[PDB]
Image 1 (cartoon, helix red, strand yellow):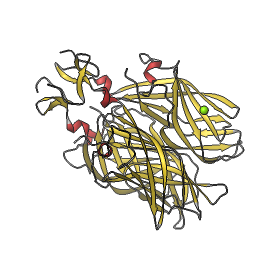
Image 2 (cartoon, each protein chain N blue to C red):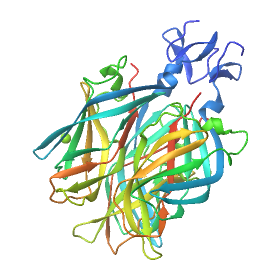
Image 3 (cartoon, rainbow over the protein chains, first blue to last red):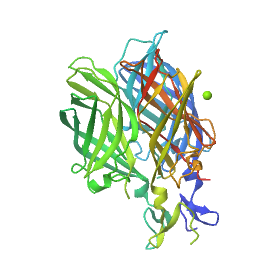
Image 4 (cartoon, rainbow over the protein chains, first blue to last red):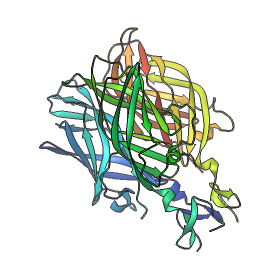
Length: 162
Length: 162
Length: 162
Ligand SMILES: [Mg+2]
């Protein structure tokens, strides 16, 4: 009775819960783009890894339509999480604070049917709100285009525990 | 308890993990300085800091600077600007003042002379912390003639000394 | 008490093993590229950091030969790890599962001796098998080239504890 997760009984002694150390799950769900009046969505099947106090969302490559210079990519965790994971388990340790967390470069191929031109855009975790994770995608300039080829992207942040 | 050692701690009467170890948020409002090949400038930024388990994350926002070299150093002066009770020493890496190539990543920097930026794909990493100044190396990707630089948001992470 | 790593005796109390919190080592070893009939290898000296349930492999910049549009970059951990680290210490928590983990942008300079053109490629941890870590490198298009200039790249993933 004397132990509190992530401290746990490990082979009759005091150890660290294996579940805290590593948990794998999956999100089959919708990624939505919105920017300067452009809107579209695509389905992705993504692995999720939860390791110590961090969650990692491993988005695969996907194809979308036009994007703006700056815009938002939103992951809807309200549906699609593999049980027993719940929407609440994707809440950041900074809750619904607005942040600039895990900012990275992502190269997106812009085209209108032909050979894509790759733009180096800037992506970060901005805000989680009621199960929707909003990622800012901006910078790198733009070209006229009708289609976007997105790379595989890993999105990571510290996960709520209270 | 006298018989527990941080980060192990009393958590609602039992043996648990200190919440402060699991998540601690702070802020740095301070000076980022660029130096390369005789070029020198500085800019003030507001940045969230998140300490999670044995890692520190410094979430730099987008900022604008002046000319950069093919290779150069970006320095974050943590001697001042940290929100109390966080102290300069709390930013020291677990590798102390070793010279490293840690967390190497792509950073796209927009170079211009006032007009539309050309983005160069540069290579950034944590190289050395010394006396409260974190030095990041920024090199590669080639260059153009320019007088202004548009820097992306960049998250700087590394293992924190204990 | 009966303590189970990473829970350990510290200073007479129940604490967290310093070994679990931070360990620094090195891999001096052979990185091999394979793609579309192209094959070559390079030697690298890389720092390794193990921090909580993560390993970080800090590859330095290196020069290679021709790459394909898509290919594998493989790290041979069977030899080259600094004692007391062993090959098994590099096994992922997802063991030998095929994954798309830690996907990121990497800019590689392609040339035939002259001025490099930088391609934004997409790199991820794909599979560890019998001491060999296989990273996928694809996307971003290509040009005709005989030489590749690779940036410093840090690759990280959760490490097995079983
Ligand atoms: Mg293959």
